[PDB]
Length: 274
Length: 193
Length: 62
Image (tube, rainbow over all chains, first blue to last red; front, side, top):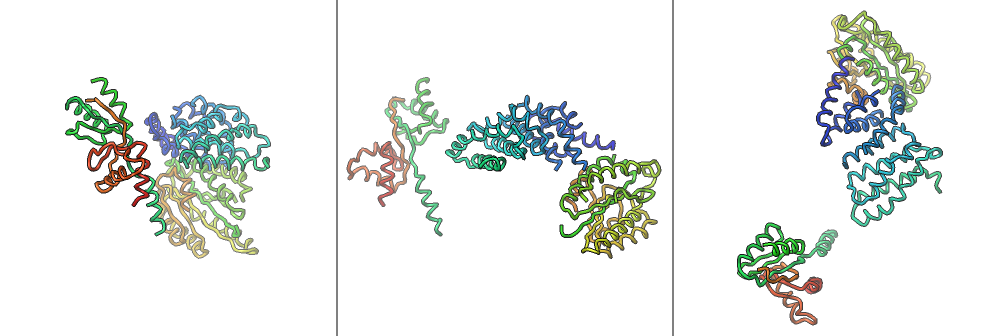
């Protein structure tokens, strides 16, 4: 028994040390998970704590029944912690943690319904800017939140959940872009939404890579420069295009050179100052 | 689920657990494993026995029963904790006795089942202790009985060296694993066998 | 030397095709507008708007 605190303690130490900057915690948190845990954990630094928080519910999957109930007891504490904490990394952590608590079925639907966290997932879901990585955890959270409700008879949350409807504009975008990953996430939302509440609701190809190559063919959009007053002004203006890497061509005997459109302006500025 | 399955778990009680310094945790893990096992199929049953230093004792005897199983196990082990056979006062455990009890139970369950169809059973030993020469005849007797019965004896050695158990798995056609990292006990139970 | 600038498109074709664009330039109707000048054998200063036409015509032509 005495050994238990010591061994697991060392990994608690390791996680503590490289807690701040990256994502070291995930593997170590898992080990930590098995061996009032939540109450004690709360004091420890947030990141990593959340990581431990995330994996522990997952890990549960007799005494087990006792464990779940025990977890249910301090679901609020984690929830209080989840908000307030709220980078992409952090954001991923907060929803991943929330998602995990949701599958556990410990969270109270009421309470969840009126909370900032639900607004935040659809907010990121709405914005085009969010990266694919944030998107997948946001999506997963939503899916899990709906999954949590196996009733909807008594679930205020399955109202706010409706917030998925807002997503369609986002799916239109995303579709416009070739972002398959984002679209798939949307479909999962839809499918899951329908699932919960469904009851309530009513060679040959050789020429095809050649036909692809016929759609690519080169030229560049470009400024030409001529009638340069003396050689020093070709060589300055030329060297200052070459360090900008936007020389398409040069001929010093012509006193003539070519810049593609993207560095017309850095050349127009250098031509004015010096 | 068509085949009834009885898995008997023999838990080595030896105070070696002190070295383990936790027994409480080991019980919690074993309980989780049992619950999963019972949940997998209706036809699964479990029996739990403790191989203590002094003697072997029955902790418990279906999944509906699990709540009962949990209480019975916690209570039974606590009684076992007694000072006698403390620490490496006694290095060995009475595995032979435990196996004998297990085979008796399996036999009885089998006869009842015989009225019906066949039963499949296997014995799992969680072994902390060391073997001894005096133990050889008794242990082997039980082992050979199991092999003849075609009942596999699997063993998970958390620590110590029980060669006889290793031999037991080989003869029996069971599985033997010496666990590196005893805290990973739950994974071994689920994954290993 | 920043005397004069001219937005144009710089075509970096091969020593085989360049002469067809020139040919395209002459002996053509509504053309000859196409090439500003031949800076190098490989490169030409050309078109802008004409580039779509030059490419397409080359495609259609052998």
